[PDB]
Image (tube, coloured by chain):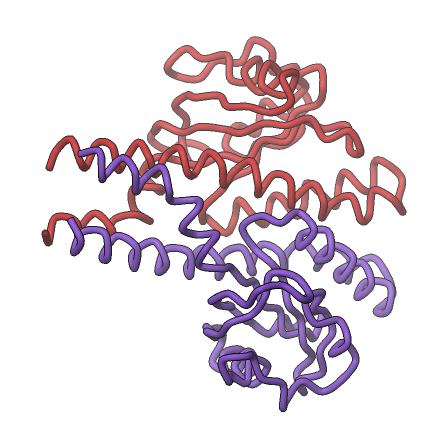
Chain colours: A purple, B red
């Protein structure tokens, strides 16, 4: 029962990793409508306003955005970092999370693992980010999820297995 | 082991139902950015062009869109239905799928279950749709998934369970 639960949990995390790669692709395709039809500055504002709305939904994912040089463009958990280089930014568990975003994007997309609150001033939680360089917007876009949330979403599945 | 696999599969389908409701909300939030700026015809063309790209991704979800009266706005699987009333449209398994989209939307969002190909001229297979009426765009937007695809995504999890 314990081995099953472990493999099941790890499997759910791996599945969510793939989900984030897909959701990043469809979000990029969506913001491309902004870039095709509005000036650069307006399109970027629209993209970041949209991402605020996603984060405010407090659902499956939370966005983070940096430019190709590591300047933070969007991160409501850490608002004071916006407009600043994030190259020396560390999570509380010592991860250079922005460097992680950039390294993953340089490979064509990938993952960064670190702890962070869900909101500014909150308790830090383990999470992960899928990041990708969108060539239309010239932004490194990260879709992120918290392990606690993945567990919540999979709670009924877990309770059913326990029942059997 | 069989009862376990059954409860697991059902649980994964119920989880996907919730995912579709969330994805529909974030897609609505995305298209609103330009509904705010452009005339209805232009904004709708942009939204449906985006949805074409989502369906062309051949990933987790496929969109279908109807208006409040059941006129089909977007359905690449059934292109001849576009611009026509879909009120009498029936899936191969005898489901008035557009009526289902509308009934679900009238309740504030919900689900319709039916068989349909993945592409025009393909073999039909079982799927479900989450639909919701978006007041800004005045469209009944449906995010849909195929059970075969959910099973594919969950294959590694299934193979691990069999491992034990």
Looking at the rendering, which quadrant does residue A154 occupy?
A: top left
The residue shown at (63%, 30%) is B65
Q: Nearer the viewer, residue B10 or B33?
A: B10
Residue A16 placement, left or right of A161: right
Q: Position of residue B162 (x, y in %)?
A: 12, 48
Q: Nearer the viewer, residue B51 or A31?
A: A31
Residue B53 placement, left or right of B151: right
Q: Position of residue B142 (x, y in %)?
A: 58, 31
Give above or below for B20 relative to A63. Answer: above
Q: How many labels sit on residues?
A: 0
The residue shown at (79%, 66%) is A44
Q: Position of residue B62 (x, y in %)?
A: 51, 39
Give above or below for A8 relative to B98. Answer: below
Give above or below for A17 relative to B121. Answer: below
Q: Position of residue B13 (x, y in %)?
A: 37, 34
The residue shown at (53%, 29%) is B130
The residue shown at (30%, 47%) is B152
Q: Nearer the viewer, residue A18 or A127?
A: A127
- Quarter placement of the C terminus of chain A: top left
Outermost residue, bottom direction?
A88
């Amino acid at each position: 029962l314990a081995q099953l639960m472990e493999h099941l949990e790890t499997g759910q995390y791996k599945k969510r990793e793939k989900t984030l790669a897909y959701m990043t692709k469809i979000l990029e395709q969506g913001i491309h409508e902004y870039y095709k039809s509005f000036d650069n500055d307006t399109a970027r504002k629209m993209a970041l306003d949209y991402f605020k709305r996603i984060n405010d939904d407090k659902g499956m994912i939370y966005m983070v955005v940096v430019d190709k040089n590591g300047v933070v463009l969007f991160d409501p958990v850490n608002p004071k970092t916006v407009g600043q280089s994030g190259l020396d930014a560390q999570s509380v568990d010592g991860v250079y999370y922005v460097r992680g975003y950039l390294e993953a994007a340089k490979k064509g997309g990938g993952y960064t693992y670190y702890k962070m609150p869900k909101y500014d001033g909150g308790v830090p939680e383990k999470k992960f980010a899928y990041s990708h360089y969108d060539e239309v917007s010239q932004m490194v876009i990260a879709a992120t999820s918290y392990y606690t949330d993945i567990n919540t979403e999979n709670k009924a599945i877990k309770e059913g297995v326990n029942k059997v």
